[PDB]
Image (cartoon, rainbow, N blue to C red; front, top):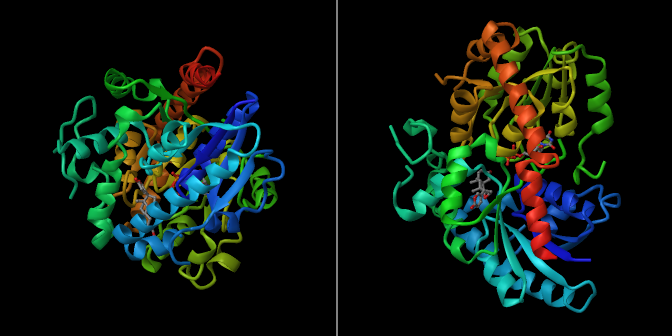
Length: 429
Ligand SMILES: C[C@]12CC[C@H](O)C[C@H]1CC[C@@H]1[C@@H]2CC[C@]2(C)[C@@H](c3ccc(=O)oc3)C[C@H]3O[C@]132
Ligand SMILES: O=c1ccn([C@@H]2O[C@H](COP(=O)(O)OP(=O)(O)O)[C@@H](O)[C@H]2O)c(=O)[nH]1
């Protein structure tokens, strides 16, 4: 049995898509060892079902994402040095056990792990967790074609400056983040396999352009559109609440695993959802409850809402009661919603979320965007009415369903992503 090592960047939007790919590979008979930091493992609550081996390495910085943002340039470099040393030591240990590791799939944000793989005699696969269109922008930043602070780039829609990946939002971490994004392509010619969590039909032209430079493998959605979650997802509570809701009546709301809204912005969102008279399921992370309005969680949301610190997002987006998804437009949420046929209300915050919202609204045509003044309740209510009631909203739903069907083709036999995972799997045999 071929033994695959997997090393995501320590954040849920990087762990989860690689985990789903690992589950697909394990179903084809590969042994998987998933390398997590101690900080990630502390939140891991369920993994006996997975049958994947989990091996921990130290965080490598003081006690992990929240330490990192205090000083991105320094602490990302300390994380890098520690991870290079600790993954080397772990691989040395795994080389004393059968089956021996053959390949290391690592997050594309850590391109320097390629040199660890090759030094240890492993193949290296860089796993890109953002779409081809956004990754192309990072390639152009590495080339100096573009510097991030109307924009035409090959095979991308014309973009406003607001649609470029947002790094100014990180203030003093701005420059450090821009260099890290561009670094994803710093050794691409030396990578053994280039894996993208997308499917061809979603971005035909830029995928074709990319494939003219390097052999790339589109293998997405990796999510299985359970063994599906590592972290606490409150599945029973969420799914029983959804099961009491009628078709097309629920606004699912989530800003992902990282982004945080100000107390004032949360007030705007809370009131927009109440004045809307729709049922809503709003993921508010535990460390972000306290910025909700006074009696919001315990009383005023009780009639129409479920406010929860984490949900089983794949199961929620697959539920017929969900009519639309108010999202920060992180790539996993965008692709999971698209593959589930769920139209979106885009409220992007930073990095690739800005560009994803543009693709959602103007290319794939499965969502509407809010306009800032902060984003006010009336703006949110207006977007909800657009999606939930208006004729335009029915068009967005039909478009989302057409993409769901194309994504279903891509991952089924003979589809582009199924074939590419097969090709990857065969190359290892
Ligand atoms: C700045 C920050 C946002 C605020 C929040 O409290 C956390 C902040 C620190 C971590 C930061 C995060 C923004 C997204 C990242 C840059 C992302 C990443 C890393 C390397 C790369 O190549 O591509 C993308 C994953 C995570 O490293 C991020
Ligand atoms: O209540 C939630 C909210 C999010 N997710 C998952 O967390 C990931 C969020 O990734 P994304 O790229 O959308 O945004 P990020 O957190 O990286 O900003 C996705 O895998 C979601 O499926 C989840 O399982 N439950």
